[PDB]
Image (cartoon, rainbow, N blue to C red):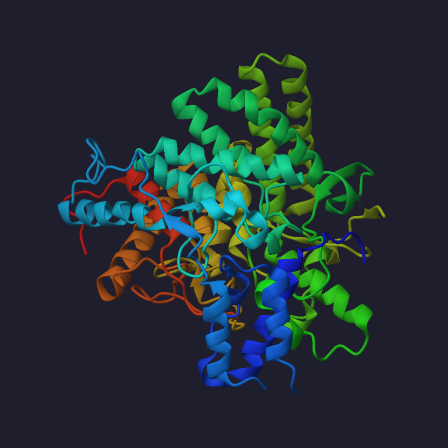
Length: 549
């Protein structure tokens, strides 16, 4: 197995507690395993003290539930207690000109409620996290954050882009900048932005949206110091994705070599936040080497931002055939194309012609890759490319994944693509006939697997990329389809909220007004990128007073 980034003593000790808890509880009422890895040490006790008592308490071959809860109450501060509520300095309950293009007053007022939830998601690490970080798995960060919500008690990487799009609508550019400052601090420390700001995430990244967050903020604020600070960190992240295990080389039929990226977690064990579920998932493998490959493919699917999906399974829907490190993903390489486009822009506005030139050349190269490696004329969409081996290889047609995913349409987001009329029409036709267009939005896949990144679910980021892309074209049919999807998506979210008073992580887009589920954890509410896409969609499209419920 390739590189592994070690975790901390605290995390491996909290995994011990986690194992004891799940062994001691009944299956019917077991707590969210991740909440044990989110504990912190209760002052004044040291790790050495607490572990010593834990060794004594478990010095018998199960621990009674009552004794375990007493122990956890005694020596730890609960999950989330070191993540304090923070009032955003830029939050305003009813901003002047907020969603002024929304004529339907019922829509506008519900959107103000959604906007109001930014307060709920706004947090800051406690002083103890900064003073003595070794007592927390929550990492210290320089600025307040926006979290996804519920069990996600920490900032996440790619979520923050769609959060920022909503923050812009919400007139919260100080909070928006704070997110990017926090993610830039992680790149500076680790070399990449972590999956999330927890010690058990230092081994991997997530879809690389940081350059897009910096671009969207600067495009409004013209904060020149931000771009000056961002450029070397974006260059560092760019090298991270274009080197080592993340870099792959695919030669096409005309013999041109294409440099592309894959996901690759630097981890080959159970994820500490899911330790027992991951062990259970791997229980059928006979050899430790098989377990390690699988655990790395699992952690790599977490790096994809899309854990989990038939998309990453060699033999779907068999979860044990997860093979994420073998996939050259469409959406990942869209984001790297976007990085090249953003970095060329920033280097131009900062006055660096040579750097701008270098990244125009790069984006031009990856544009070629999309036309040759990913595109499929017959399917009218872009397909993930599955590696033949681990070493450069030659493109084979049978290695495109012909299965149908919302991510297959991610490249429509890119301007060189959505500016191409005759390409856009082919993609429109493919999307219309794909079966991904459902009553509430775009299905993330067509296979009902039991996993959350599969049918019947749809997901805010994937809606936004397709809607923005189609909506940027000049093709009337694309623009009308984009608006229709946006309004179905808004409506379903409005209907879910009337029943639950919450915004959900994912929707069951096969049915209007239903939230989605699946996967190893219960449906979560908040919800960062879901709120952001609702607000961004309403800003773009408004809601005419005549159209309604």
